[PDB]
Amino acid sequence: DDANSFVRAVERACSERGLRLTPIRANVLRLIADAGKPVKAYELLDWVREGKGVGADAPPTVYRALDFLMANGFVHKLESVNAFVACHHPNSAQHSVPFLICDRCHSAVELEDRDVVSQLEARAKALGFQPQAQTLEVHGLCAKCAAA
Amino acid sequence: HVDDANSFVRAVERACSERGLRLTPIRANVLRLIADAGKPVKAYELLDWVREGKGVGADAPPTVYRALDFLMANGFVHKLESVNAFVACHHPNSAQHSVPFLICDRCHSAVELEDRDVVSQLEARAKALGFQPQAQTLEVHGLCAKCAAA
Ligand SMILES: [Zn+2]
Ligand SMILES: [Zn+2]
Image 1 (cartoon, rainbow over the protein chains, first blue to last red):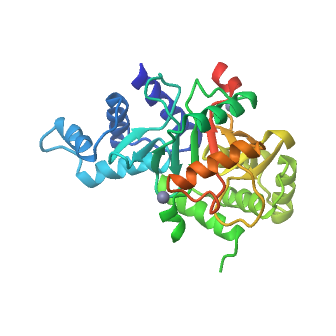
Image 2: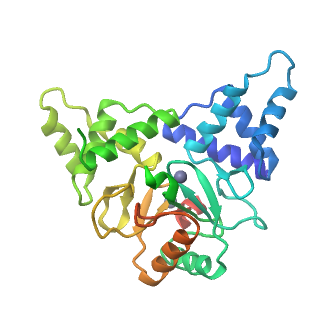
């Protein structure tokens, strides 16, 4: 229900935004949702292929589906560990620390300064948000994308 | 070719290409109107400007509000609750004293983070983690208490 909660929020978001979930995009979304942990690009391709030997999606098609999710902010690249993670959503605890994500490149870094976060979360609760129903995200621009 | 608000419209158009979104004329029209205005814009005002820009044949109000919902749902435009008016996303090099926004990802309502102490620390942490808080003001994304309860 963790994974179903993620799929439902992205489907709801796509409906609202005018985005289209083709079959591969829904397939990839489901595999990422059912992982519940960061995913390597090679694991996603293996999983997509596990269905049919010959009738499998070509790798570029699989990775364009992953880029679609990243570009729309449903998935980030945790470059810490060279893997892909679902956006924060109304999910469980025990792996929830805010993400800092770049607008252009969709890499994420985890904000691990407990008192900066705690202050940020306090400000947001006072201002009408629920930092514990959904872990916050900070969105900005990385130094590397800023250089161009 | 493109100055500073024109860069913003360009980058939204590029983002549409990478995301799988269609930027119709009315969507580009409302975006450019919001971007060129500097100050938050009321909805009735965009509707005014859209009619003034076109004249005979103007888009009906439902078309203009749906284009605004498109822009909000995709995070290019927020509704600033305090002034009940719309503002562009934070974007690169807009030259001003801008402050970070806190946006609900469900209703697209935003509020400014006016706590200098908390903002200063966040930007300091972001600079330490590899980001450029001066190249583009930070946004914080969360779920509002009202949207959470519904
Ligand atoms: Zn980047
Ligand atoms: Zn809300």
